[PDB]
Length: 89
Length: 89
Image 1 (cartoon, chains in turn red, brown):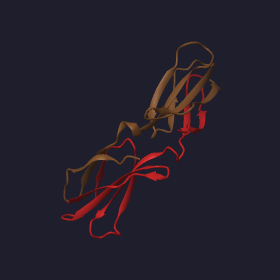
Image 2 (cartoon, helix red, strand yellow):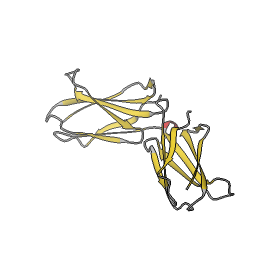
Image 3 (cartoon, rainbow over the protein chains, first blue to last red):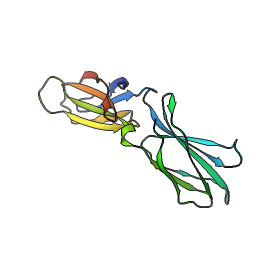
Image 4 (cartoon, rainbow over the protein chains, first blue to last red):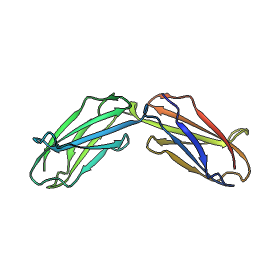
């Protein structure tokens, strides 16, 4: 929808140059992944990830515990309906 | 907005899990950068990057030449009007 914003060539030498830009929040299409012990609802950790990530690895988990993990898409001020999983370490 | 799809918990250990998902192509967003000697016919290098990369670095330009640079956003089959910047090496 929106063109990239800012936009600056920097370090322009004789044979080289760096092109720089931004992207608005408008089209910043993102993944959020929340996770925590399932029956402690207040314990939720959020990870935001680039649209291009297709996986993530949660660490520092407690042995023998059941976890819930919730997964949404986010673009600007629209979010998807959540997608929930539950697993037990 | 479409949620993440598939979605599996894989490789559960006593302290780690792996979450996996994918998104439909429809929803991916990148930048298409095109650059070349401003006013000369032909050439051009065109690069497509993911929304993750805010910068890109270019090389093998001619020592004291004007270039023009064009950046479009892409989300699916839609694109933006371009944003364009000339510069002289």
